[PDB]
Image (cartoon, coloured by chain):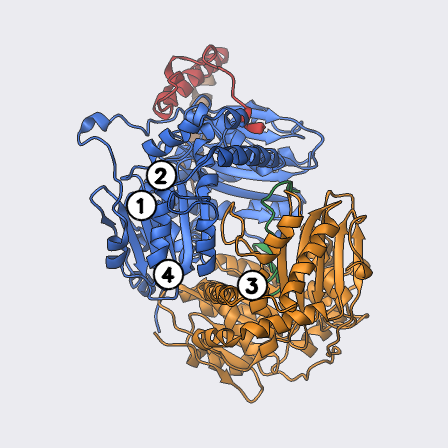
Chain colours: A blue, B red, C brown, D orange, E green
Amino acid sequence: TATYAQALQSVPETQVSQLDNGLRVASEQSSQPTCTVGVWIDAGSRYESEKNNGAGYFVEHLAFKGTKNRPGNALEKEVESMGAHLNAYSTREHTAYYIKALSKDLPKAVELLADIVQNCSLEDSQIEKERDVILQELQENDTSMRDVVFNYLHATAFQGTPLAQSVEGPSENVRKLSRADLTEYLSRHYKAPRMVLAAAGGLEHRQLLDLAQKHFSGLSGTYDEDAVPTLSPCRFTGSQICHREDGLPLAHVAIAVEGPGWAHPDNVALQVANAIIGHYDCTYGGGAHLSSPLASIAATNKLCQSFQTFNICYADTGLLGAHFVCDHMSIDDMMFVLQGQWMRLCTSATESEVLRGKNLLRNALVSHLDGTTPVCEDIGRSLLTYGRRIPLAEWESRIAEVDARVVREVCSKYFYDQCPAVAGFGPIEQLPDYNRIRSGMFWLRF
Amino acid sequence: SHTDIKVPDFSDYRRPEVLDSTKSSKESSEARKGFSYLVTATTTVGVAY
Amino acid sequence: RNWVPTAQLWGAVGAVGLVSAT
Amino acid sequence: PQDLEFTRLPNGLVIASLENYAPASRIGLFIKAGSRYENSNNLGTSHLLRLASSLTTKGASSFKITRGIEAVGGKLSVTSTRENMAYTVECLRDDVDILMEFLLNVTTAPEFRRWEVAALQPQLRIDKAVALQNPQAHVIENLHAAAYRNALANSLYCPDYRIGKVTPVELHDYVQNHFTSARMALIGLGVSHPVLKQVAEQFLNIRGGLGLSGAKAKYHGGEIREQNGDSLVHAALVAESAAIGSAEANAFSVLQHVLGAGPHVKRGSNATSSLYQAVAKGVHQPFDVSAFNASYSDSGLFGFYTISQAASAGDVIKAAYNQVKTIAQGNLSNPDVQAAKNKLKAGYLMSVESSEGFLDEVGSQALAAGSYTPPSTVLQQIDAVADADVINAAKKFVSGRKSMAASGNLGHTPFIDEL
Amino acid sequence: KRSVLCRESLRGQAAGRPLVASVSLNVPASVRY
């Protein structure tokens, strides 16, 4: 026998350690066969200027095509013949390259990764081959209404800030982008302390730490003159950006109010509140018997195709709300039932309700951590986000502190009378007027 | 293509309190709701008379 | 829940309203 | 710390259990009914049953079942393939018992009510509609239908003309004949086996022999061709694979991998992929291609899958065939089979490095062999393949009755006689 | 529908035990290989 709690306390702690330059070394051990070593660099899309808006994102395409030590196909053929998989993902705040492999392959793994971060053989040919490809990718991104709409939400959420640009990077910059510029970018932002080299599975921390090629380090200040935040707040703006295209079949709306950064008591409590609203699809087996009254109502009344609440965590700001897809004739009822669930949450939360949304959160947050790659991520990212902590076991404690009053007062700070940030892509003709959305944030009636 | 989009300059229309490209508006706007609701409040109270 | 508090302010309002108004 | 524990009962149902360290436990009853279990008259029942898992059953109403699991933050997947039907159940360690009572009513006392089961019918169109947005799904389906004549050919998705027709008796029957003792395998990834077996023994004892459905295997080469207006065309070309869990089989998987092009690298292209190199040289700029490998209990299918443009269709299709023809003409040096193998072995472990993978892997063996082979032994078997062996199996594709399936503008897609 | 114009294509089906596995869950739903 063994019980949830117990389990929790019995999970393998994460070892954070540090190289002379500030290379961060984490790892969770399990002594099992495949490993997923990763380097989680944290200079993303929000450091890019207007020009280099998609500079990082470009580096990514180059990341795996050569290293002075491995021109051409070397990288890949090396990864392949081992049977390892190599992925690059880039956000607006975090770039990240990682390797999945057999646990005995660390030797060559970690050497490869480290090689990748630093030496990237980039010729005029590869730059001009990657331009054409990203211009094509942009063209394909436009085909995506989810993507197109969430970009919009950031743009308008954060008008006139560096964080509202498209990771992908503004079309034409790609054309223009000077070859020198990639350098400056990397040089300036790939310098840990920023980066963390994390990993999970069968490895011994000890070795990891040791195995980190100590080759180049942060070329930065020792005093406060660095102190000028590179992470300067981004100004919060409650606008809408409506982009009508009656030629498209369905409607995409992203509504969110601004939230807190990565680190905050209120930020787990929010999750438990989104637990309650939920997330629903054309294919959910429970339709009408779902417990989230939003779900139930679109299930029952064919009100929507798919909706999903989200909490987009950033340093200086956030994005928090729902997103729904639906017919052109359904936009307003969807908007009604949604905001209505928000409001009823900050004024009428019941202990039963919060209690269920609590538990859900536990599970979402345990189940994601199944597997080596997920666990890597948690570790890597978790150290630029929340710093070095591994709050995993605390969670259940923190999660457990939620009496429904907690969930309700937390909820009202962000939602109640806050100006929502709205974005949709036609047919939006029925999408509420900004003033209607707004008064949808208080409760006189409706 | 959809990325060459830029939200217009709103500086002219916005105000004092929330005009800071690089700073929080959350510790600004608290009042900015209160002034506007203050006008309502008054309006209502006068009209009541 | 929040109804008592809110019903209490709503009861206040009606009261003072009559009192004064009337 | 404790390894799994299989147990075959008097009934013939297998059960396993690993008390893991972590906070997540998932049960998952695998019943042996696939899609291959229906007939001309039954087609589409598997599918509706799969979508039918939260309807009223003897001890639990559809409301209680749904709300129940929600109360606790639990999942209930119902998954199925052409051979089997995995009903999965995930939840927290403390709630297994509330959940397992759910899994038992859903599987053992389903009550298909005329009104509840009609209400669902529509759902089949919606489901099918979404699944048929990936050309892979219609082609891959149409491949099975063409290469098989009777059993494995019947797809996973209800036929358009049978949707509203799938009556309650049908689902009853299908449960009673196929969801039985001999065909099941309980699996836990964080349960007590002593307590699991008690429960097993109390709730899973029902009789039913195989193929009250019409079990049997057969391979017939055919082509099924779907014209579209889409710029891209997908085709598959496949011959009878080796059977499940046998040497030949295993030899195929190895060879599959020598050509097999499932990018290991993001934004990366394969240097290792022979098909890709070969195809790529006689091919245009834009194009993608991969070896296809499918093994089931009584048959298999092995060959490749192309995605070309209108006019390149043929060039890419024959390019890939020609290169697989090279391996059957003998041409294949040792360096490439070891790589392949390591590729495979790395793959299988990663496949199992996850609870949900592990549980599948275990439940699957349960239904094929009768126990759980450990990873190590598995790794040994793949290794035993002979460099030649691969060649030999390859010789078989080339000299094995073809069966192909495409989708798109097909003015440039070889027919059987074309290749 | 998502545009399939570039090199990016990498979809083709072949896993170990499972092949063309379609899942319908009470919450999520999908189509794998």
Spot occupied by residue D48 in the image (x, y as percentages of width and height) = 70, 63
Disc 3 versus disc 2: nearer the observer: 3
Above/below status of D84 relative to D76: below
Pointer 1 and pointer 2 on the same chain: yes
Which residue is located at x 31 percent, y 45 percent? Answer: A196
Tag 4's secondary structure? helix
Q: Mark 1 points at which residue?
A: A196
| First-in-chain label (4 vs 2) | 2
Q: How far apart are marks 3 and 1 (CA)?
A: 34 Å
Q: Name the residue under label 4.
A: A105
| First-in-chain label (1 vs 4) | 4
Residue occupying the far left of the picture = A223
Q: Distance between the residues labelled 1 and 2?
A: 8 Å
Quadrant of image for the C terminus of chain A:
top right
Q: Mark 2 points at which residue?
A: A42
Q: Name the residue under label 3.
A: D257
Confirm whether residue A405 shows in the render: no
Label 4 marks a residue whose chain is A
Q: Do the residues labelled 3 and 4 touch (CB within 8 Å)?
A: no
Q: What residue type is labelled 3?
A: His
Tag 2's secondary structure? loop
Q: Nearer the viewer, residue E13 or D173?
A: E13
Confirm whether residue D306 shows in the render: yes
Q: Are marks 3 and 2 in contact (CB under 8 Å)?
A: no
Label 2 marks a residue whose chain is A
Q: Do the residues labelled 1 and 2 touch (CB within 8 Å)?
A: yes
| A59 left or right of A290 in image | left
